[PDB]
Length: 161
Image 1: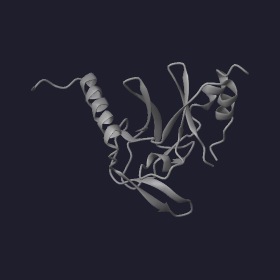
Image 2: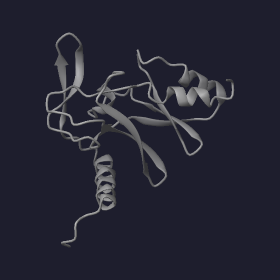
Image 3: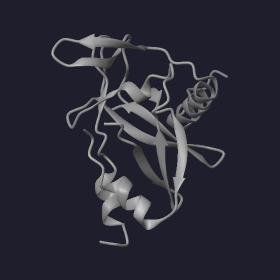
């Protein structure tokens, strides 16, 4: 197999890698830390390249089916027990991350000026919410993403608006 691996082949391999990490729940390259002037967050312990899978946002998947419940989701503010939500294949889902686990995605802080972005990842039709590096990230940096990145698109599509 000496032929140069395609950009497509690499993405296919990374999809397979991600499926397995999501299956295993193995998490490498991050730790909880205490940050001076902020408190608890999650930091990189190794380098991440722009576009690298960072962590799954792991918790309990809940499907939401009525307009009122959707409004309740959409009207949320990033600041506690914020329930991250998304649209997938004409369904609405949120992830309840309130159970205490060892899975670290739930502990990554919110920022409008972050270094990670969310992405949906399909495993046999089941959407998984993962975090991806928006740029090169150094060991030692706090991981941050925008909790509100999907709100505007969700709100605009709501039947009551």
